Image (spheres, coloured by chain):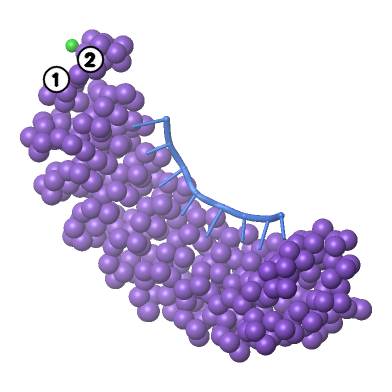
Amino acid sequence: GRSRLLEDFRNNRYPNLQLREIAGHIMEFSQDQHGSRFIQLKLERATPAERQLVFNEILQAAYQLMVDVFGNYVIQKFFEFGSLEQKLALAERIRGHVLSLALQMYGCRVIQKALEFIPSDQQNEMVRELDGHVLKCVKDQNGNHVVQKCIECVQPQSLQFIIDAFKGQVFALSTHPYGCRVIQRILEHCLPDQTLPILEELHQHTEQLVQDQYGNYVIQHVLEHGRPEDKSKIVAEIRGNVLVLSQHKFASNVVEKCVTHASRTERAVLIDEVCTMNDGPHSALYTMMKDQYANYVVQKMIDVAEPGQRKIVMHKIRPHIATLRKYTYGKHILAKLEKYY
RNA sequence: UGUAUAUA
Ligand SMILES: [Cl-]
């Protein structure tokens, strides 16, 4: 099965083996773990002629290397360190196979690398091959990384068909484990005509989303990178629910990003909400202090409060200082206190 | 004291 040169290579009998010595043997070495490593090592620092000898033998059977557990790294190197003509010729071997490669455990790493290094002409052809399988790729554990890469690498206008597919389905995909990744990328790289409709669906489902295992991340993303108009829509959704959302394992993270990224006014209003409104005998603030998640909100509020409003939080906390000690999460508030005493 | 992405 393995050629003598390969076995003898494996068997450690050529510590001085050079690329030129494995002529006629690239495909075999490429599909072998040590051989493949050998080839990669030698490539990052090989003369264009050496790199060309190696290419000549992988071009025809390229696809086979792209879907190989060991060969995919060799292809990838040519996409990184190869030549403009070499990258274009592999781009051709890929044509008509973008879909099946992007759903492939190993192939999809090659599609990702190709998208980073080819011209927009070839990018746009690759993308177009996904026309009609947007949700299939987004839900696939291989495919979704290709869709994220497209979004990061290709002109936003070539991605309009991905948008068309997310339309009406944004809530579904934001609570999905891969889809929430793609939604975020669209928010970062897509055009106003594109992020607009998506932002609308997001605002429509903020209540559910902030509480969702994956959805909260999309809401936090908007808070950290979005337009003030969008940040405020979200903040308004937290208003009046600060206490409850803070005690939630997922929503409490979004509450923090609210306190942190909200306008001066909106921040003061949120902090005041739990200073003022009561939760039974003592205020919302006190209940939050004792809670496994809420105590993190308290501390972050202490962090970003204007010096004047920090005074008010401190005064509300102060009467309980001695009793906080007796609570698992209150203790941690005492910690943040020292910083400011 | 608290939540998310993949190959040797
Ligand atoms: Cl031989």
Q: Residue flagged by tag 1: what amino acid is it?
A: Glu
Q: Chain of mark 1?
A: A
Quadrant where the C terminus of chain A lies?
Answer: bottom right
Q: Is residue A316 above or below residue A144?
A: below
Chain B's colour?
A: blue
The residue shown at (46%, 81%) is A227
Residue topped by disc 1: A21
Image position of A148 (left or right of A25): right
- Write down which quadrant ligand 1 falls in: top left
| Quadrant in which residue A215 is drawn | bottom right
Q: From mark 1 to mark 2, how far is it between C-alphas?
A: 10 Å
Q: Chain of mark 2?
A: A
- Lower sequence index among marks 1 and 2: 2
Task: From the top left corner, tell me how far across and down residue A184 is, in percent.
Answer: 46, 65
Chain A's colour?
A: purple
The residue shown at (34%, 41%) is A107
Q: Nearer the viewer, residue A135 or A174?
A: A174
Task: From the top left corner, tell me how far across and down residue A294 is, in percent.
Answer: 74, 68
Image position of A125 (left or right of A135): left
Q: Is residue A96 above or below residue A278?
A: above
Image position of A297 (left or right of A38): right
